[PDB]
Amino acid sequence: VHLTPEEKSAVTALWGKVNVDEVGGEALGRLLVVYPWTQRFFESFGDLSTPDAVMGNPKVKAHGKKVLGAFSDGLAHLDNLKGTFATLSELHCDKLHVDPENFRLLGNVLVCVLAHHFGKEFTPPVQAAYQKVVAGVANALAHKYH
Amino acid sequence: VHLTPEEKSAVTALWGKVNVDEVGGEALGRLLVVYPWTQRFFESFGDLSTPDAVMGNPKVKAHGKKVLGAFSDGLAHLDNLKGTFATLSELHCDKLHVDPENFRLLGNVLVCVLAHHFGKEFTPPVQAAYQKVVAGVANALAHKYH
Amino acid sequence: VLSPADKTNVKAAWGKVGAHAGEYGAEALERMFLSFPTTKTYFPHFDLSHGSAQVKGHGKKVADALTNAVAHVDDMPNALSALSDLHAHKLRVDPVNFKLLSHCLLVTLAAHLPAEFTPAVHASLDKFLASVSTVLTSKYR
Amino acid sequence: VLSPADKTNVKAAWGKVGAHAGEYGAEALERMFLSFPTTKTYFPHFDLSHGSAQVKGHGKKVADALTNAVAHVDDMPNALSALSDLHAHKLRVDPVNFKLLSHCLLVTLAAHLPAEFTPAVHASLDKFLASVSTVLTSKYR
Ligand code: HEM
Ligand code: HEM
Ligand code: HEM
Ligand code: HEM
């Protein structure tokens, strides 16, 4: 997908303003709490019986760091996303056996967390641009399934 | 997607056994009756208030003929489906504005009608092969959306 | 939720189905397993061959549960609270696979019942199975 | 359907929302229109600019309907039978767009309410909006 120069400048500015530690942890914790069946893959991380424990789990943040790093790399390489999201796509298709709905669910949760952190600076144009970005990343990462 | 020679022989035999007149009409009528919101595009065809009128509408069969012809062409060209389903994909993306769920709904309805007509000859292996075929056709036809 | 016409059609369809429920359920399980191999990871202790005793028993159990649900169509939560708790808390199954199972059941009952599989019965069965899956996929109490 | 904790959380969240409902609904409409341009074909007689009087009025009407639904959370069909009939028989809208509207509403209430948008409130609002959309998308009577 193509983006206008103004949209590119806006998304680059906000991403530069993003704190790169707690956003991924918040996204993962909110996903696990809101959609409970997603714990079938993360049950190896320890206690997840209550949202307090889910948010306080250290492995949740330790994995959200890698998730947000992957998102940052994908955002850095927007022109070629299929080439960048190849090994991850193969891993998800082969070992994890995850249907592609969870990818868009995680993207929506990330957009919600971004809006929560940035407040009124999340204008509708920037929200649309980030929706396009997350849709592109999800489609690139889930391609072998269909 | 690749198919084994035995699956190819089975699907070719059954498709050769298919009646090429009423299957498309039955598929379209069953789609319209089961999922009522799909009439938002076919409201130009006349009276569709009851399933009896929906099945008796002549334009329903006259359009099911073309739908089944397109499916037959796609089945004939299995190796290259993106090249074959290009103009139709552009038309559906531009003018009709149809989300890709209706494509898989129509594929499932077609498989149900095939099972109904053929009875016990619709073995689980043939059912799986036809599911693969319809999934491939739907994915090839809906590519510009995502 | 459901119209009286839909309820009557569903009751008539299941009454016509009758005592072939166990075989129909076993066939639906086999069809699902062959068609979609991504749902075979929920049964790691089974022997998913053809004509398996364990698969036949599970199909019979599913058929009996569906028959009870039909007999209590207006009281789905009270009838299937235990099943809902087991499927939501212990197994933790996503609601995608219920669509595949419903479609396979529709195909199975369509293959051997050509006379009773009218468009009205098709719509009624679709809505009834969707309601059953929705009731079964919930987290309450 | 809904737990008492979820009901209490939803009631508290909407009570905190209070009288900003009209502006929140208008903002949700604008967000949906900008984000997804495929849902602009249901409004062919509107002027979908920024700060439009008609868009503001429609947002206020949507907000009032949502407030009534909150006030009658346990009686959704009896409260919204007319809306369900209008949305299912006349307009004939597919249930996909309700997900987009719900997500846009969630974003809108998250942006302006950082204190009350805890994970529990997030889950409660998600389930409540899903239930409202499910009730509104039906064909009964
Ligand atoms: C949507 C964008 C996503 C991205 C960019 C992403 C990226 C990643 C990355 C970078 C890893 C680690 C690779 C490594 O360590 O070598 C990973 C593994 C994993 N992913 Fe994803 N992922 C996404 C979505 C999801 C979703 C939605 C789920 C589940 C619902 C999921 C489940 C997992 C699991 C369970 C692991 C392995 C965790 C572990 O081994 O401890 N991923 N993914
Ligand atoms: C799933 C496989 C599908 C195939 C192979 C297919 C194929 C076709 C073909 C061959 C035409 C006519 C093109 C022409 O006349 O030049 C057409 C048009 C059309 N299609 Fe599709 N289609 C599919 C799915 C759908 C679905 C699911 C819907 C709606 C829910 C739909 C709605 C329409 C409409 C409304 C028209 C125009 C009818 C008219 O102009 O009278 N199609 N499609
Ligand atoms: C759609 C309607 C369904 C009904 C009516 C149903 C009903 C049942 C019943 C009656 C049992 C027996 C529980 C027991 O004996 O303790 C059961 C267990 C089970 N179900 Fe379902 N089920 C449905 C769908 C599914 C689906 C779609 C899956 C997986 C994709 C699934 C996975 C399981 C598993 C793994 C068990 C445990 C089997 C065992 O422990 O031997 N169910 N279900
Ligand atoms: C999700 C919750 C929704 C609620 C609570 C809601 C509520 C309402 C209300 C109160 C009206 C006023 C009816 C009247 O004044 O006669 C209305 C009309 C309408 N709604 Fe919805 N709606 C929802 C979703 C949607 C969505 C997602 C769409 C389209 C994508 C939609 C399309 C329309 C249209 C086109 C009208 C008619 C507007 C007009 O005639 O001026 N609604 N709705």
Image (cartoon, coloured by chain):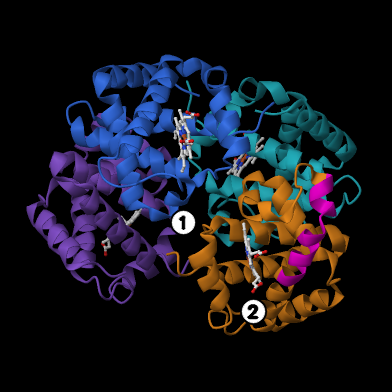
Chain colours: A purple, B orange, C cyan, D blue
**What residue sits right under mark 2 in the picture?**
B3
Q: Can residue C53 be seen in this view?
A: no
Q: Was residue B62 drawn as part of the magenta stretch in this picture?
A: yes
Q: Residue at x 38, y 43 (%)?
A: A39
In x, y percent, where is residue A145? 48, 66
Task: Give the camera-side residue of B67 and A95.
Answer: B67
Letter of the chain that mark 2 sits on in the rendering: B
Q: Position of residue B28 (x, y in %)?
A: 73, 58
Q: In which quarter of the image is the N terminus of chain C?
A: top right
Under mark 2, the amino acid is Leu
**Residue type beneath disc 1:** Asp
Please, which chain is the residue tagged with disc 1 on? A
Tag 2 secondary structure: loop
Residue at point 72%, 26% (across, down) = C73
Q: What element carries label 1?
A: loop
Q: Seen from this angle, which residue lies furthest right?
A: C115
Q: Where is residue C110 in the image (x, y as percent from the top left)?
A: 81, 51
D87 relative position to D52: left or right: right
- Residue D139: in magenta span: no
Region in magenta:
B52-66
Left or right: A144, with A26 as reference point: right
In the depicted structure, whether residue A15 falls above or below residue B70? above
> Label 1, on which residue?
A99
